[PDB]
Length: 453
Ligand SMILES: COc1ccc2cc(-c3nn(C(C)C)c4ncnc(N)c34)ccc2c1
Image (cartoon, rainbow, N blue to C red; front, top):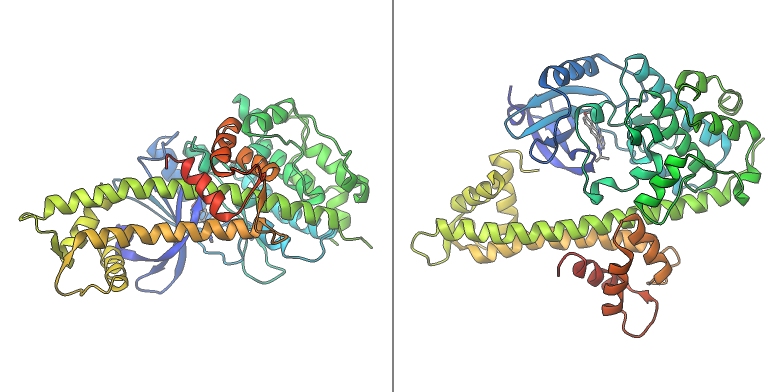
């Protein structure tokens, strides 16, 4: 069976672990799905074919309200296609920051759901390993919506990217035993423990100025409840967190046993709002998302440089008599050529080409100046990535000051794991009045200089 025979791409939902996720539609039934597309070239397999197939077959038969539903699996020469249920409520933390109040009852209800899904998967000998807030989606945009955990089982079969754009936020949540190589299902309880700690204080239990500092803290495994925010918190919640963040996994509480914990039992059946926590979470989330957006912007810019020159070279070769004129069918064949080395098949490329032509007001039916088409086709993704970066900038700038401070930049570039000396150097080239702050344009300029421009 061939993936594109059955499904058509509607739009890109976003980038997740191991690949891009595309909102697709069944060509016959009209069923909408979220399809994780894994590039074989970019992502190595840890397991063999037989093991992956069998795992997938198991996953298709599994069903739990807090676990992403998997429907289908396809494989071609270059890609794996993982077809799951699409959820519309977004990421948990993005919903949480929008609330005016948040309590231990809300936290407990969230964690019960996570523990329930984890418990179910563990019974079936499937481990997540890379559990973190962005793997917790909300089923719908309804305020009470169920949490759906994504990416269970994948890290067993695929090697994680070593690129920082893919690694953002991973360090806070990873279990110490995962770092050292001997791990089991208990690693998921640790990660859930870290998440709970963040839910109740707004701060990561294991924090640091960069990835390695964070990992160093995790590996030591020591944390405290000495922040001001922890005075508002019950003893039972801290007791649960202690049991989940127990270093030796055999001594660590299981997911199932955690569901029976006093805290869970008590708070999921009066409590104040954790206002300090909500504020800290807002700041945490904004920082994480800006760092991510920063790396993606730089990556998209590099990709644009690559693709612009490749596309130009493809069309030059095609342009036999060298007058710079190509027809739409040729533009499609060359765009396909670029894709050959989102655009899952020929019809997707036809549409994209048509969208570019309709932007540049070039007639679809005559011969076209390809150099102009190239510019617009690329420029489009350029304008686009810039818009998502800007939005993340505005979001982070909660006071609408229009600026980010040098201290804030340190925090952002730290999470993005950009070398301290390097960004300071680029900051010095842009900030030339010792202002100690940058507006959006300036920030963008820094990122361009941080990706060889
Ligand atoms: C193991 O097989 C699968 C199959 C589909 C998957 C889809 C998503 C997914 N990501 N996103 C955006 C946050 C980028 C989603 N948005 C809505 N629904 C989704 N289902 C996803 C994640 C993991 C998946 C794993």
